[PDB]
Amino acid sequence: HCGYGKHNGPEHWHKDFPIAKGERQSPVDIDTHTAKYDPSLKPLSVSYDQATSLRILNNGCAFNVEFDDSQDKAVLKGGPLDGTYRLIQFHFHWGSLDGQGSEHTVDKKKYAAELHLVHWNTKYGDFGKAVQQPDGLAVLGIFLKVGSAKPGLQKVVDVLDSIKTKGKSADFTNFDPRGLLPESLDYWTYPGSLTTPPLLECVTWIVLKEPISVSSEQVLKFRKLNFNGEGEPEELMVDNWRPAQPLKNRQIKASFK
Ligand SMILES: [Zn+2]
Image (cartoon, rainbow, N blue to C red; front, side):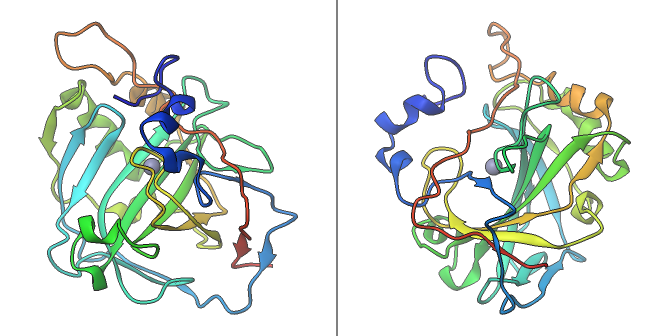
C-alpha cells in the first residue's frame, strides 16, 4: 500500500521495494550546466499518427490513458533508442500548488506537473517482460507550466468527472496524443526507473526541454480527482510525485547545444 501521504509516501517505499535506494532511480534533477551535448544522438521520431486510445482509468495513484499496443500503431524510435518502442499509456504527476508537481526538476526548478508517455521495447514481446529489462521502456517526459490553456488536453480534463475515484474507468477512444507535445523535441536523456512501485530500473528517460502550457482551470480539475475509492473519505489526488533521487554513477545527455 505505497502511496503519497505522510505515512506511506516516497520516503517509506524502500521498505517494500528495496530498489528504491538503487543505482539508477528516477526522477532526478537535471542540471543544465552539467548535462553534456551528445553529437551521437540520432534524431527523435515520435510516430503517433495511428494511435488508438481505448480507455482512461483512475488507478488510485494517477489516471492512465491506455492505448492499443497489440501492433506498431504509435511508436517512439531514434534518439538514444535502439529499435522500436510502443506506446501503451500516458499519465501525469501534479501538485497541490502551481509551484510543485513535476518529478524531474531543471536546475532544481519544479513545474506544475509532468506528463509521462510510456513505451515498451517490442523486442521483448510484451510490457510485463519489458519491465524486467534494463532497456525495456522508454518514457517521454513533458513538463507542464500554468499559463495559456492547452487545447489538446481538454478532452482529458472533461472526462475526469467520470473517473473521480480509484477503480473507475471510462471509454476514451479517438484521442490524439500529438496534441500534448511542445513545438521542440529537444531533450535530455539518462537511464533510470519507474517513479512508482515497483520502481523497476528499466527506463530510458527522454525529457523534453520545452514545457507545454496548461491553464489554471485545467490543472485545477486534475486536483479534483480522488486517491480513494467511491464512498470512502475523500482524499484529493494531489502531490502524486516522487522527489528527485541521487544521480549516482550517471551522466545526463542533451540532444541540443
Ligand atoms: Zn509517471
